[PDB]
Image 1: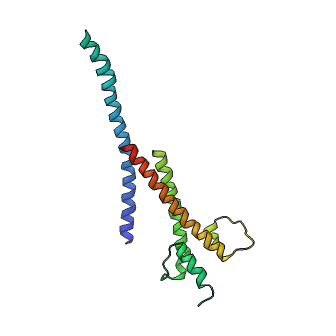
Image 2 (image 1 turned 180 degrees about the vertical axis):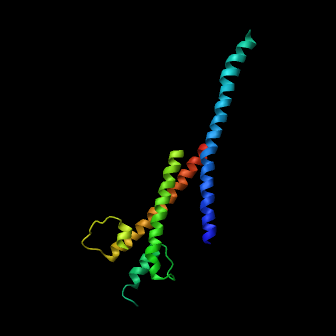
Length: 51
Length: 51
Length: 50
């Protein structure tokens, strides 16, 4: 029981670390897609297609 | 039938200590509960900061 | 036991057994309340991630 409780605490610490890193990685992806949509598709490419 | 049985029965139930446990365990158990409270507060603060 | 639960060396001149049971109930409630807050915080976090 004591060993399983220690394992539980370790797993919990790891889970908390992963929950801290995951949202930041999603935000970086969102930032890249936003750049592609706003700077490339709505602006750069739209001007090119018009000309 | 001990004079203080009813009072301590109430204390054991309040701290969620089983009645079969030895009376010498009550202070150690309460100390651990306080330790847990500190840990939970620290976890909440860390998580609130992370969010 | 009373010192361990109340923390506050407030030299209360008269310690009662009823007071002792109340402070013990408070600790249990504080732990339960903290666990509930953590659960809420975990939901908030999960919503943000979704």
